[PDB]
Image 1 (spheres, protein in one colour):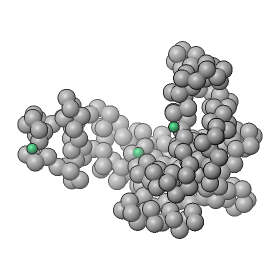
Image 2 (spheres, rainbow, N blue to C red):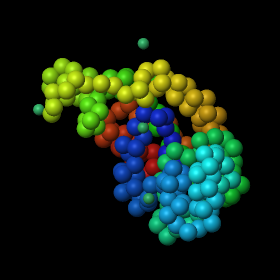
Image 3 (tube, rainbow, N blue to C red):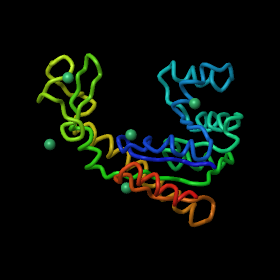
Length: 214
Ligand SMILES: [Cl-]
Ligand SMILES: [Cl-]
Ligand code: NA
Ligand code: NA
Ligand code: NA
């Protein structure tokens, strides 16, 4: 079973990763994990990836595809794999096709932007400990205060609404053509594509996935 799992930053697609891994007996792989691990191995691909990153340079599509091809040839991908958050562009998806890396399912984990914004901007944090509260989902016991220390809660610059919205805008401009690419691949019979409603409770999403996948 070969699955691509896509989703907007903050949508929460990772909430279903362990269910998929345990359903098929397949690992979760990501280009980020490949890039951070490339150094650990002695492969020449990894050394080439190390030097790119050490020079602050962009990882080219050709290199990332090589790393993906390398990763799925490892023994743990014999039942398949859950490719998390890649491809990100049409040129990357075509490079997968050029390399011969087809998958059985493309899952788009879909949560509307407004709900992602609400989830993130409602966060309140105790920065010294990393404790995280949410005004609606998990409020502090005492208003504005960390339960443990009583210190006044703050918010993160990375969670500012304008910053989240800019991130989502950029995501959809990159991902909309990719989604259409995979829908066309599915109409051609090369793969299966499904839009997954990620606003439902996790257990209901899990059930939905069972119906989509089999
Ligand atoms: Cl997320
Ligand atoms: Cl307490
Ligand atoms: Na891993
Ligand atoms: Na959309
Ligand atoms: Na506002």
